[PDB]
Length: 369
Ligand SMILES: CN(C(=O)CCc1cc2ccccc2nc1N)C1CCCCC1
Image (tube, rainbow, N blue to C red; front, side, top):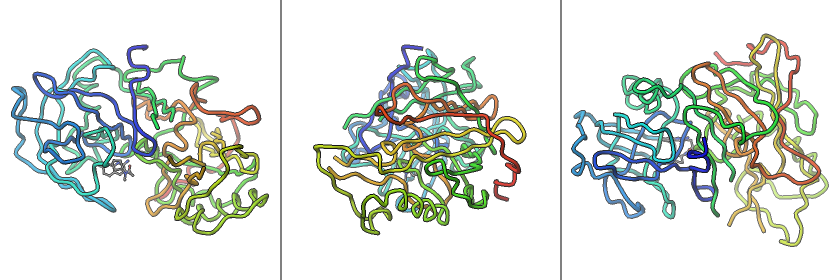
């Protein structure tokens, strides 16, 4: 798989993008890899923050579907025109496909001033595809129209960030130890169930249904470990406690202040490891993934951001979790797999782990209905 190794680039906080081409002749764009959504959507107008944008008038293989899409979200929108064209991924499988494409023609707080990407790649399922599930997501089209296997994996290494998106298989050189799989609970987002949370090998001891209220998902497009509300303060409370070897203001933990140290020495030890238990492949079986403080204390370009934060929408295992591990989205088998990443950052004392099996009863009761 070397061709696809290291095919991802980005900037701290600005996401991961892969190079893609659209239309005939090919028009190259940097597209952001997002497992949190299901639309393939790209800039078509000369927005001032865009380096490049899709010029449909140049493409003989462009086809208007004569329909629009409106995608509002919490603090922003994008809006555009549906059509189809031929899509290819240079540092990826050697194929070319006809995919749905949303020509973005108006947006608000969508493009990042500074960033170097011009569209988004929705890697999740039809159910959450805008405007409706009849709009076949890109990856569905790829597997349907070639012999590329129904799976992809992501190794986010994290100014310049890099990684790999291995379309069609798994590159063993990218991870150590063993993959452990958690089932994709439903095919809309990459929904999974967390069955237990420790902070310093010490159970948070909360009703496990809290952890997946209303949703726990895996999302390359989100930066933070975002936790649900109750869970969040409970973790904070425990994190706050394990970190009593020093004080910080309330606004910090709340993601309203930065927190400053001296570029002489990185402390680290006074911060707790976080363990998440995820439902295993078998009845009553689970496994745990373990992040270090390097994963959740993120330098801003010497003050870091506490990269765990609260949420209304559920749990979101963002880059914080994902850069710890090789993540395999085994869509063929309705499961997500986790292994200790080969490129993740680690000191000499502690390390990110994927360990099992453990015994965990009533795991299905941790889901929400
Ligand atoms: C707020 N953002 C998040 O990723 C949070 C969760 C998320 C929201 C989305 C909203 C609309 C379309 C796709 C989305 N994908 C996501 N993963 C991003 C918006 C898209 C580009 C990067 C910043």
